[PDB]
Image: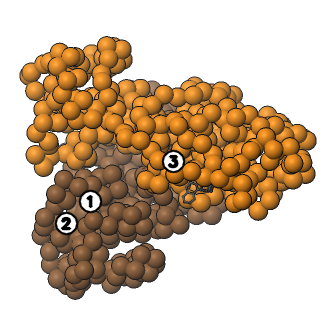
Chain colours: A orange, B brown
Amino acid sequence: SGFRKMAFPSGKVEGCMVQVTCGTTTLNGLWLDDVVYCPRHVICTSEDMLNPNYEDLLIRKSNHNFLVQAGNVQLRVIGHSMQNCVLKLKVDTANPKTPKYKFVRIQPGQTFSVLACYNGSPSGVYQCAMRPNFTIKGSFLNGSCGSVGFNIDYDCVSFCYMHHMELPTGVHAGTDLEGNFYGPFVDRQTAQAAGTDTTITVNVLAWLYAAVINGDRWFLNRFTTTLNDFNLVAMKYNYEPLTQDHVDILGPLSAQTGIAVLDMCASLKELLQNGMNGRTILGSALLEDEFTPFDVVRQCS
Amino acid sequence: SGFRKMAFPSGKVEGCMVQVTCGTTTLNGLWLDDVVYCPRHVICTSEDMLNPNYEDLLIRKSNHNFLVQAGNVQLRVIGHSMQNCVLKLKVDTANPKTPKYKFVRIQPGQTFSVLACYNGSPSGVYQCAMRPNFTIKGSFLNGSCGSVGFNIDYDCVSFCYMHHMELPTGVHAGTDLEGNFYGPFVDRQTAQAAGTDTTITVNVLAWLYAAVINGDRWFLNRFTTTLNDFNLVAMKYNYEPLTQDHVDILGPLSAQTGIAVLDMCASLKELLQNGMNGRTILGSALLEDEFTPFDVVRQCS
Ligand SMILES: O=C(c1cncc2ccccc12)N1CCC2(CC1)OCc1ccc(Cl)cc12
Ligand SMILES: O=C(c1cncc2ccccc12)N1CCC2(CC1)OCc1ccc(Cl)cc12
């Protein structure tokens, strides 16, 4: 029993983290086989931040201009390349601790574990979600660029996020590991801000199932609803629409609990309209939307 | 910026986890140097659970009765000993991945990271707190006994918890690594239940400081209070008393924010009396008590 914001074990990723310096800028890198991946803005100075031309900034750069440090052992950079917003630094040594890995891009609503790192040193791990507005509500201080987000499937590490910057609301923005930003954000100094966010409905439903699985059933009702009528109320509360594919995905959880998906949609509608009346669900006084249906099955089974 | 329930990286501990079988009971063990630590109830059967005599149950046991599996590599058990509620299994091989470690016992109010494991395999990591009633609100399923809780200090792993059982409220109980239970719980079948819990006041204060550090200041007031008058209100709300040593510990945070500790006690008193009026603090609609003052300084600095 119990329900916690549970991250993946981070050992496999800890062994890939290195420090990357270029100029006076130091950040983190990800060392897999004989390549080190890092944010390309490592090559920038305060001057070139309003209108950087990274193609120009990188052509004026040489290999010896990059210091890579795996702990104390310095790795020799024998090649440099830019892939979108990431820099790829070819090193003389293949990481002996390279796990079986994959570079995957995730969808808004999907979750991942973050290994916050500073100077190539792992500091902490936490679970995060890609918000509908393509930002993440992370925990990051100056020096954390290059920290990675990831999921573990079997023995395979699916890297999905590399950290680049903090937006004005205190939220975070970054790229997949191929260097392509999540959301409409750029690695240059601008007045960029996160757009309006919504609630990840299918996740709130997954979390209500987790609650029931844990014996919290006070919010349950005998009523049911149609997907259409549910969606008509959800949108008034800034919730994303629920699709048939979302109800199909919640099928295992519905079977394990004996509560139909549209039954649980009816309970949600009432919670939205009446609130919780000073009660809590799984230790929370608001509706949690950063657990996917998979996250629940994984922790509750 | 940001504030998350952040665990320690778990790599150092992942490399210590093994599987322990005795009879048809399989659970997890912790392998450090040439010793494997695990819950002693591994040696029990359903029959001997109402009145087990572990001294008798272990004398009738032989070394070959214990199968230890580090992944696929079986480790040969050359010795067995009981230390309070833990079993120590001397093995022929010293764990090459043993980190610098220490066995420490923690206090109610202190936090730690949990590496939930099943069949010796790390499944997930999460932050937990030792409650005032000596229980933890963990996340654990059948098969998780022997999972460990720990803190990392520099490069040293301070092990503080080994998981033994689930209580009826869905909360968890266990031992330090010397086999001594946290709280008045025993490793035998009884109607044992968690006693009444309280809120960890100094932690709620630490978390309010984290909020201010993150730009959430709506709950702040110009009023201040005395430690006595604050404690007189807190106890009405089932909060633990605040001591001078607690205010001294919150000194760094008070200095960094310019909010006196008793100023922040005044804000807390008002939150307790009026509630939050539909507002949130660091993404929460209730007052969070599972972050210590150290946890805040570590994540916010
Ligand atoms: O290291 C940080 C940072 C990262 N995350 C959270 C933070 C919170 C407070 C202060 C710093 C951080 N930088 C350094 C690099 C950064 C973002 C902040 O500056 C200017 C800039 C321009 C373009 C990019 Cl593409 C990244 C940056
Ligand atoms: O494996 C679990 C377990 C651990 N934690 C959470 C759980 C939630 C649901 C079901 C099981 C678990 N056992 C097995 C060993 C256990 C506790 C539950 O049974 C009887 C017993 C007697 C004494 C002890 Cl000292 C431990 C046990």
> Whole-percent x and y of residue A36?
77, 41
B291 or B31, which is in the foreground?
B291
Position of A193 relative to B104 (above/below): above
* Numbered badge on residue B271: 2
Q: Are marks 2 and 1 in contact (CB under 8 Å)?
A: yes
Q: What label does residue A192 carry, if any?
A: 3
State which chain disc 1 sits on: B
Three-letter amino acid code of the residue under disc 3: Gln
Look at label 1 and name its amino acid. Leu
Q: Nearer the viewer, mark 3 or mark 2?
A: 3
Q: What is the quadrant of residue A243 in the picture?
A: top left
Q: What is the x, y in percent for residue B19? A: 55, 35
Q: In terms of secondary structure, where does tag 3 sit?
A: loop
Other residues around mark 1 within 10 Å, as few (<14) / some (14–19) / many (≥20): many
Residue at 37 percent across and 39 percent down: it is A197
Q: Residue, x 21% and y 16% (percent of image)?
A: A228
- Residue drawn at point x = 63 percent, y = 46 percent: A187
A81 left or right, relative to B14: right
